Image (cartoon, rainbow over all chains, first blue to last red; front, side):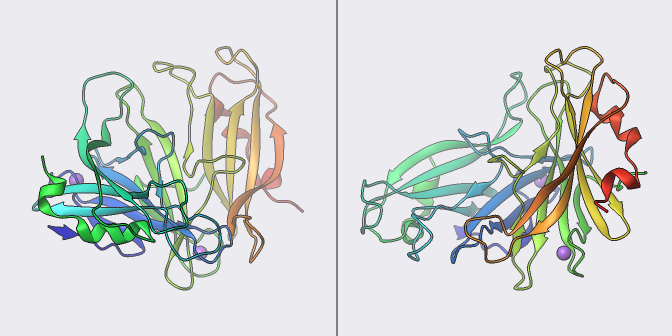
Length: 157
Length: 158
Ligand code: NA
Ligand code: NA
C-alpha cells in the first residue's frame, strides 16, 4: 500500500494496468481565495491514441474537487486521494459527515475501484465505482487527516 | 483561418501568452455510444508551478464538450474550436440555435478571449470571456461546418 503523491499538472500513471500511461492531472480552481480547491482530472490512454476523460461518479462533472467550508479556515470538508496496491489504483474520498462541519467530527472514507464497462449503451467506458464506505475511527478537524487510517484491508474486498 | 492543430491528449500551448506553457487537453468521453464526445480542458501554468483549471463560461463544468442531438446522429449541435491570431488564442463555440436542431439551420459563433481577473472576489482568476457572438451567414446541418466562416476580423476586438 502506497498513497500516491501527485505533482502539479500531469502525472503519468497506469491506472488501468495495460502498459499505456494515463494522465492524472492535478490542478486547482483559482477563483481568488486563500485556499483554492484542488481538483483531479483522469484521462485514460486508449490504444487508438485517443484519451478517454473519466466522469465523476454520480455527477455530470469530469473533475474531482476538494471542498472547503468557506473561503476562510484551513481545513477540508471533502478531499480525494489516490492509493495503489501493486498494480491496482483506488480513489478514496474523505468527507466530514456531521451537521456542524466546522467542528472536529466524524469522517467517511469512500473507496472507489476502476471499472471498465464495454457493453451497455450510454454507460461510461471507464469510471470510478464505489466498493466500500467506512467511518474513520477518530474524529478530525480536516477530512484529509483520516487518510492516515487507510490500510490494505480497508481498500480491498 | 486554419484552426490550431491539436493532438489527442496534452498540448503544450501558451494560451495567455506569458511565456509559460499551459495545457490544452483534447480528450473524449466514451460512453458506449456510436460517437465519442470530444472535449477540451484548459490548464493555465502559474508562476508557483501550480496549474489552474479554467471553468467553462456560464457553467459549472470544467471541460468544453461537443454535443449531439442523439446517440447516433452524424452531426454536431454544438462544437468548440481553438484559433490563434498572432499570439492571442480564441475559443470559438459553434451552436445550432433553432428549436428544430435536426434540420439545416442557423448557427451562432461565440468568440471567447482569454481574461485574467486578479485578486477579484470569488471571480475566476483565469476565464474565457465572451468577446462577441455572430450569426453565421449560411445555414448548416452540423455546427462545425460554420467554422469555415471564421476569420481574423471575426476574432479580434479592434
Ligand atoms: Na493505461
Ligand atoms: Na501561459
